[PDB]
Length: 137
Image (cartoon, rainbow, N blue to C red; front, side, top):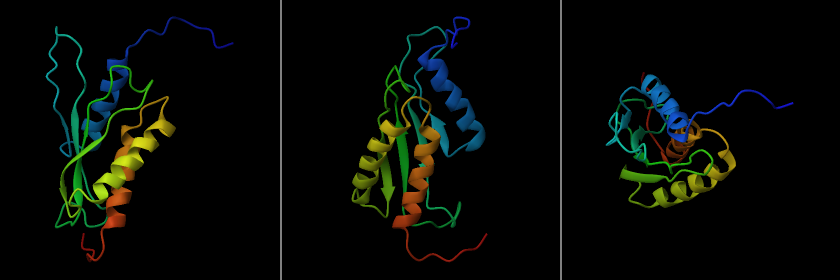
């Protein structure tokens, strides 16, 4: 089996598919950063995702980092890059750990879109690295 029409999408389509879904999910924890215009060369879909330790919510919080991602021009056929900027709590300390963890999780997730998993895994990790903090909300 496995025969059918020429499904002929492109990597930037598969990519921007995830982007549109992120704009719903987050709204403004998301920013796209693209220099893209209609009628231009393709370039990396650079985005920013603010991510936090679950529970405390959009409130005081302790640790956080922004997730910066560009994608290669072939993602998800290969793994994306991952960079963790403007960290709080983590003085570029366990940032290294999580970045390295994500840099492996990406290989496991390779074959389809992984950004949504990566963002979940960060919010696990941050909540892990977070200690003390009541709940309210």
